[PDB]
Image (cartoon, rainbow over all chains, first blue to last red; front, side, top):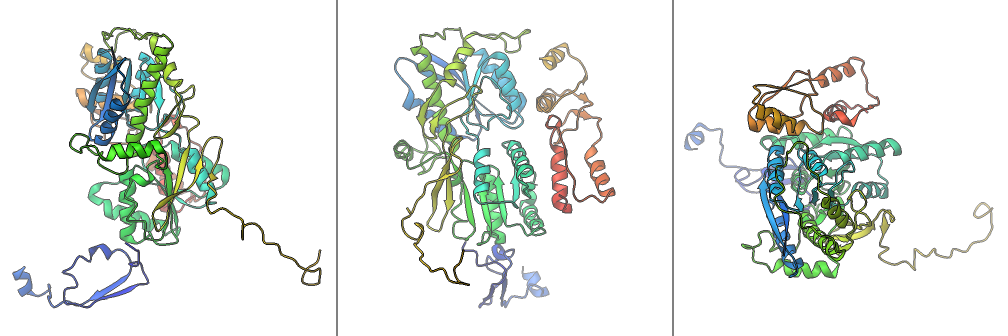
Length: 50
Length: 399
Length: 100
């Protein structure tokens, strides 16, 4: 809303639910966004569970 | 005593219909009361427009209120010119001077050019839609040719909803091939809102970007979300809320029951509905003037076939058009006057700028007052030139 | 009026012309009444049904001819009485190909 998601800003999400939140709306802003996740969707076990 | 009028309302114009009904209630008089022949069709369909026009002609309405689309403006103009039935419409004015067509919407091309010159713009992008035609695009291209501008016109309405997000992203990324920072949004309010959503999603609403909303509905949109971004946003509005009449109407407008008057339980009214209300006021004043001039409209409602060969003009249609063009009243859209072509004259358009606290007026424009700013924050210190004294001494001060 | 008279006659197919001020009416009438319209006029901007357009789309040839001469700066003298589809095409190509 205040336009601080533009390129030049860096954000770190300090939780293990980085992609489980609604981070889509800042994907195209240009600011670098990072975080952590404990759920690895690339695992066969996680794929079967999904 | 009742007077027949025809209504061509596009489907979904709930607020326009509500304002039409409010105007009918306000301006009705006991000596003559209006009766509408409301036809709700797809206004873009030329066949539907012809069918509605013929249905209203068979009922013998002396005047027709409604709207037209880019694919139906020619039909309305030709039918009105042939059958001598005056058309009252808040739609975009015709590029050519077509008789029996009355325009409530003022010309904003001159105001747009004045605003562009005010910001001393020379290089800017132009995102346009065909909804109101390409007359504004033609005018801005001619002004670019005369004033040596670098207008980069991009069509914004040809995209589809299935690829809305990706098309606009590439559109704004193609702008960075020119590093464009100045953009004018020449489209209706929903398209402007979609463009603002795409901008705020991609973060081009930050300070350094400048936007001009090329319509008379600047605050009728959702510009609140772009208010805090930092990019300068400007536009035009024909509805001025500082007027006592507009304030009283808004007080009456907001208190109405929503189920009875859909789209009316709002603190703000779109310029389309306001001009719909003012059009009812104008044509009621036209009939009042015609009756005061002791002219009669007793032509029977059994007009007959619309497509008779040859066509049948009626003399009283010219009298009704003359009365309509003779109307000079004060409405929600300010002063209302018409020229020989039915286009509005002596109108005053307000120019708004979007600040942190909200939109505010900065100036006004007219055909005799080109971009006259309100001179807020009156001078007297640091603008009344400070008296600088000095001594003739080289190399400091010398003739 | 002419289209209505011919439709009342019951013609199986219709041949005719149009301009920017009557193309929409013809297209709408043909789409509604389900009558083919054979026309040598300029192609319609949209994909309107029931209108048969023999005139080839010259926008592609014009753009390829501009690209053949390696043009990047030119004037465009156009008549408004034949549709602005070509003008919009040349403007969007200029935006895409960095022309002036």
